[PDB]
Length: 115
Length: 115
Length: 115
Length: 115
Ligand SMILES: O=C(O)c1cc(I)cc(I)c1O
Ligand SMILES: O=C(O)c1cc(I)cc(I)c1O
Image (cartoon, rainbow over all chains, first blue to last red; front, side, top):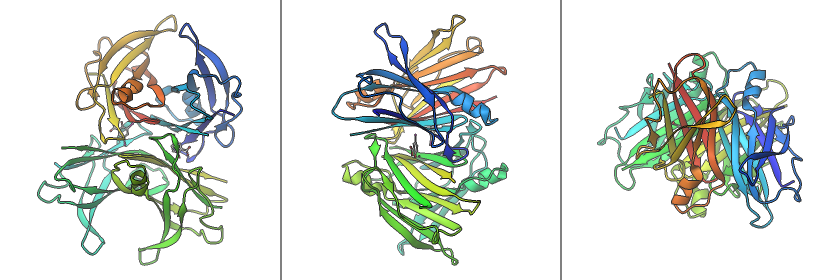
């Protein structure tokens, strides 16, 4: 489990549940190729996206479908989605958590990268 | 104006207007003595809290009355207020902007300090 | 375990380890009485602060000693500490996670309150 | 100026100066067409990206080159950039401020939208 995505809701003070998340890897021609996807659980987490074998060094994009999340709650949002773009580097044994904290007109995102 | 407070609303995507702000300074006796107060304007900014003369070295607390803000809009938020505590002017006079970005169950705060 | 505190480091992209955390409850005379304290673990979490029996309705303050954290890393910080002040309400079965994401001149804090 | 970009540095407590910003607009063919670009000033602000005439309805992407910013300061950050994607001017012209608060492993972004 080298990659996990976590989403929190700053309006309700809760995990953001059933948020669609799409992960892409940058291809040689510079296009974004689908890599993994899922929906956050009751805990706002998405586990099992990839394996150590498949998660090679490269540039990844995590798209979080914030607009549909807010719409499902009957709340008017600003962004189309939240996008997190980063390079995975084999600087020893590392697990990546990409987290996002959501408001209708704002989001924060951080990386928690641990052994 | 050596001290300015700026407040934004992350739900509406707007300045946070009419937010009450109370500033305290730690006294010789180690208690929080009233220093200044005001409310944010239409721009979400609060200017004119103090002067270069009065804003001496000290430990300051800026209390931003976020609960009263959300309640005046008919919303029940999590926090009582947002308190920003910092040492000021310990290396001579600086200009401090204390900024806060508000959601019902979350806030962010930053400082912009200039010479 | 009705209360947990989590602290993350936005500079290193890691849990904030060995951060001192002090929790207070507001007393009848309006003073802050010590309630619980600890240091965050390797995961940046502080568990075991209180019990269901002791965590009655009231106003609580969570003080996170951010200044000492940054100093121990050799980094110059802005704030004395981060303070989170909130009312605990028995609106059915609820667990409170108070989380903070730290930078030298900024922090964010959110509440995750779940059944 | 209907579109402004503001960037702050959460490590230094300062405007983020000389940050490159590229704006794209989704074309009829569903690709990201170059729209405007510039760099933040000493105030951390980027004005004059566009005009009321040219800033028509559309889906816009504001790419803030955070990696280049941190690298120019001799720091190795997590993200490649911060991308802010939103529909603009769908209910007539508005003024948009897209703001970002940067740390090496984290960023926050908000919008301030006025009529
Ligand atoms: O706990 C988190 O995963 C978390 C994530 C973000 I992004 C911001 C805050 I405050 C948090 O507490
Ligand atoms: O524009 C601001 O003042 C601003 C203030 C905070 I606190 C966080 C973000 I993102 C901002 O953009």
